[PDB]
Amino acid sequence: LGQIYANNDKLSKRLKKVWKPQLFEREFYSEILDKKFTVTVTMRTLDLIDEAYGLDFYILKTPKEDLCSKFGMDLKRGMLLRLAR
Amino acid sequence: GSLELERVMSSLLDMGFSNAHINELLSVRRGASLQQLLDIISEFILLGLNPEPVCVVLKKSPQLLKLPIMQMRKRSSYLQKLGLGEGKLKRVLYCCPEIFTMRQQDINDTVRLLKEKCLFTVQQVTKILHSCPSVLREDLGQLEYKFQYAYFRMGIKHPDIVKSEYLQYSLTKIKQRHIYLERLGRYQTPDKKGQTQIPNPLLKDILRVSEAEFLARTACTSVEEFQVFKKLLAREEEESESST
Amino acid sequence: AYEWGVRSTRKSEPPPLDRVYEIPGLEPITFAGKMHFVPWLARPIFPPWDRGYKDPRFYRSPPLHEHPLYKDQACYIFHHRCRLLEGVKQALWLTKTKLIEGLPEKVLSLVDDPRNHIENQDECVLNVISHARLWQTTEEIPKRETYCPVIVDNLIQLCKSQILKHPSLARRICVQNSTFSATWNRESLLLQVRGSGGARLSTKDPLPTIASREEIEATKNHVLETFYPISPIIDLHECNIYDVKNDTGFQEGYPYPYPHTLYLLDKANLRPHRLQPDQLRAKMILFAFGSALAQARLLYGNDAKVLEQPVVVQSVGTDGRVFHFLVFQLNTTDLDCNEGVKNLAWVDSDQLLYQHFWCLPVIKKRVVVEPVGPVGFKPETFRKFLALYLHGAA
Amino acid sequence: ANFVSWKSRTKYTITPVKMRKSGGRDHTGRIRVHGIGGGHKQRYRMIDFLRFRPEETKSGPFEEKVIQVRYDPCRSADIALVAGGSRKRWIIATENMQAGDTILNSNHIGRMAVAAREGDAHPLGALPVGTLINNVESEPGRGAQYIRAAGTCGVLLRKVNGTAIIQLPSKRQMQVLETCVATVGRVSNVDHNKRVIGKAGRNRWLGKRPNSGRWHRKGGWAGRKIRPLPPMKSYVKLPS
Ligand SMILES: [Mg+2]
């Protein structure tokens, strides 16, 4: 949420602008949880999963300030509990 | 294979095709699937075309056979939706055989241009398409300029231009004849009130008639003067276009 | 095609469950502990709750198919509120009866002689009509629900005033709020009749047979009329939960077991609520057949056969001014097959006691035109009413 | 706004249904359509537009008998109470349907076209070409949606390989399959369009509020205003 100058000119009018991410629904399988989850994600999330080499690795490695998802943190707690127990 | 051949011959017989007719569709077909030939004629007659007009158009343009059936149904539905159906299809198809080959978008914005930008009624647009199939090929810019040229400089309303088939005539030829009359004093642009101090010559004798009689009746001048004016007029237009 | 009930008025889908439940091996944190809702906590799921004790003010019935009296074979029930679509024609087919126009000669013969006539009969009937429709209550135009029952009651009381001449009239009484049930079959169709309403005139002696053996045996040649596009069980209450039972409505030992006359009233203020004359006549036939069938099964057993002694039941129906008279005689109990001996029924249709009644004077240009009172009173209607009442007893 | 639609009934019946007027307002309480309000109170009679609706225990074509043809306050056409088997339902009556008439409904498709009688329901493929047809449906089992007004009549033009072309009263073609069902003939109340209202009071009875008194010259001109081109801008208004 922010402002944009029309035609990229400082002397033109200032207009409100809203930028929204592109959302896709995909199917993900968790090795630790032995379950398949249908969760809406973005292209950035898929890239992060690929670099982390697995959804479980991506969930367990990424901190909470970068996950930005309560569902993702709940996935981490369930994975950690299974590993702990 | 044989049973397929018997079925299509039977279907053509029920659909109104003679034995002389049926065999010459076969000659026109060049490798097209028999079932793809069976339903392409089905959509054409479903549209409303009579048997012998169909045999004409496809034999002039055999490339219509090598077309997906799905797009044929979408195009056929679109043609019926816009008010084009039985009888009117023959005129638009013969003068513009490439109607089924072009995309839906260039037709979409053309009628949108006519209905919204040119402010034509739904019935008038259908009459324009039927009477003048050549409006589809050229771009929107010169058609809008042609329409507004008649509306403002000639002062003629919508029912007159849809009845006289003014749009089908060349922009260059109408400019030469109208400007010459206006400079001759024979034509006067209607004022804001719509009142002309002199009787405006009817659009029919300006354009529909040949230049020899047009010069003799309305212009009342020698042929070589018009030719000199034509070169003069063409000079100003290319200067005006270069300036703009 | 087009389904009834818009989506907006339909029950709303409960909101989706929280994704914490999808996580295996995780215990959700809900607001069920604090016993109140908060938005920042998971929504708990609640196991189904059962009261555990019976409460009549909050009782819930079990499912229909779990009821003890549940049968796969549907039974079509005719009750007081049923209105047959084909009227008498449908009624004849259901009852397997032959219709005869006009009352029996023996019933009518009891009135032709002037001895049985009531003294000042015309004057007494007119005063009864006037009191019912004009002198009944404080208001000036009594409604149909008010005078329709009282006009029949006063007619019965007027007819009951003949005990002086005929002491046998002391063996009959009028029974109110009496119900009866009867069950039978018609071409592999389970049919039941549950009569209600009106007044039941009961007597200690069964009515004499009206038709002879030769006349009864003449019903074999007669055939039942049929209607193809409409099923005979149309406009009938079809229910899969019921009980097959035949009842006369009275326990064994009742002093007046034989029904004499059934009186039916169309006491409805609104014309749409009022039954049509054809539908009203069909109601009498079905009720009379049910009363006759219940008596036949009670006396002659549950077997389906031709009765050696027929059962005669009379019926009178009216809506206040238009009267219908029916005499029903039941001859057989084997109604499964349409061929063979059939029962009989004599009917009189649309007998008007009076064409119209003026509760207020009609003033036209300050001139009285129609005085208060009945218009076109027909004394022949009461003669048939008197004949039906005096039948058997006289 | 606590607005609840009255069309909440879920089971079909022939009993008239009490209904409440909207007055041109949507569920938010704001006016969406102008000129609607008041009028005589009306009771809704549910109409079965699916002519071929066999009973639960039966199947296939069935005969059907007309009981009474009366006037529907909620539509221009006249409705007919028709009874068959052990049920009754409301349908739309054609030009000539009276009490005692028997009408057939059939989904059977024939090798040859069957003779079309008025009021009967037959598939589009089982009807002769050129018959008067009302109460058509887009797809099989959808139900009648088109040609429902009083006196309207469509005509079947051709059938080509399982698809039939019908002519709507608006002089526009439409593509449907032969498996769709339709009613033979034209709707009743042919003289409906020639009725004269007589006075402004009658229009208020029907539930129509008067038009706005504003002079909508701007609205008329806005829908008929054109933008001159830069070369033509000098010719838009020549002073007299
Ligand atoms: Mg005005």
Image (spheres, rainbow, N blue to C red):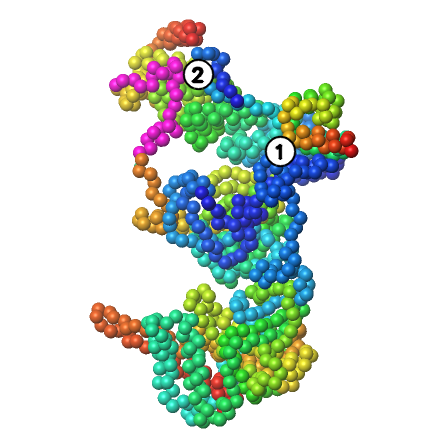
Is residue B51 visible to the viewer in this orientation of the structure? Answer: no
Q: Secondary structure at mark 2?
A: loop
Report which quarter residue C286 is drawn in. bottom right
Residue shown at 66% from the left, 77% from the top:
C334
Residues at marks 1 and 2, CA–CA distance in whole angstroms: 59 Å
For the stretch drawn in magenta, the main secondary structure is loop
**Range drawn in magenta:** D215-240
Report which quarter residue D28 is drawn in. top left
Quarter of the image for the N terminus of chain D: give it.
top left
**Residue C37 located left or right of residue C361:** right
The residue beneath circle 1 is B41
Q: Residue furthest front?
A: C34
Tag 1: amino acid: Ile
Q: Nearest the camera: C126 or C42? A: C42
Q: Residue furthest left?
A: C366
Report which quarter residue B143 is drawn in. top left
Residue shown at 40% from the left, 74% from the top:
C147
The residue marked by circle 2 belongs to what chain?
A
Question: Is label 1 in contact with label 2 (beta carbons under 8 Å)?
Answer: no
Residue shown at 56% from the left, 33% from the top:
B77
The residue carrying pointer 1 sits among few (fewer than 14), some (14 to 19) or many (20 or more) residues within 10 Å by Cα, namely many
Tag 2: amino acid: Lys
